[PDB]
Length: 90
Length: 90
Length: 90
Ligand SMILES: OC[C@@]1(O)OC[C@@H](O)[C@@H](O)[C@@H]1O
Ligand SMILES: OC[C@@]1(O)OC[C@@H](O)[C@@H](O)[C@@H]1O
Ligand SMILES: OC[C@@]1(O)OC[C@@H](O)[C@@H](O)[C@@H]1O
Image 1 (spheres, protein in one colour):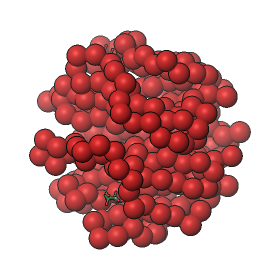
Image 2 (cartoon, rainbow over the protein chains, first blue to last red; image 1 turned 90 degrees about the vertical axis):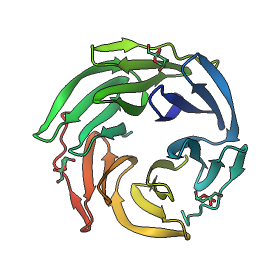
Image 3 (cartoon, rainbow over the protein chains, first blue to last red; image 1 turned 120 degrees about the horizontal axis):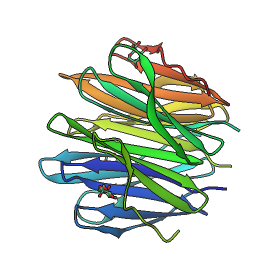
Image 4 (tube, rainbow over the protein chains, first blue to last red; image 1 turned 180 degrees about the vertical axis):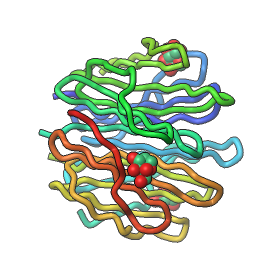
């Protein structure tokens, strides 16, 4: 009956991204040290998890969105979100 | 029917913090390389997620606790837990 | 009615591990920069969370699997998964 969140962060400011799944809809709230705002991420899912890493000063993000037994990976690589190649025989 | 956990860690020992939401109550078990113990975190929530970063050797933690459509951020910055400024129009 | 995932990553390639709990069974899909494959992790749980850290170039992983009010820690330290010492009075 409650929403579910995943979070990642990078740097020392830091930057934060919080993802929230809500009735099959996943949104993103972001923080970069000046204020909270709403991010470009809007994707279907009943559950979400996230991890992130830095390549120099480039941020790369992977969000794992799941409806039922199917799980989809979304990749941020600085040029808008794109679908990843993840798979599973759940 | 089961409890839900989130975890973060830092350093090389390392330090670990595991957060558990249980019937709207969120507790914290901690590890610093000598034994598991119970942490100062005790907050209302049906769901939890966490991220953390280091500023030199200072640890900063952000825990995201959710009941229903409302989500609250708690900040550790070395001086006890305090409420953060996170928001969302869920 | 949906599966639940947790994710961690390390390095710059990077390496990714995605954990999925599905009807009390937790599996692992892995990525090391050449393709997605299925990992050695197969453990009972209705919920999962993960964190990881590096000691030089050695990866250490901690997965937190939960059925009901009981929560179990599994440790990867380069020599196969082993049970950890975590505890809680949930
Ligand atoms: O497209 C980006 C990608 O190749 O990055 C590495 C892994 O996250 C893959 O699942 C993903 O498809
Ligand atoms: O008070 C600490 C704070 O400013 O830190 C950065 C963000 O986590 C904010 O949501 C939070 O309120
Ligand atoms: O056996 C490995 C271990 O000691 O590593 C540190 C902590 O994760 C403990 O819970 C765990 O048992």
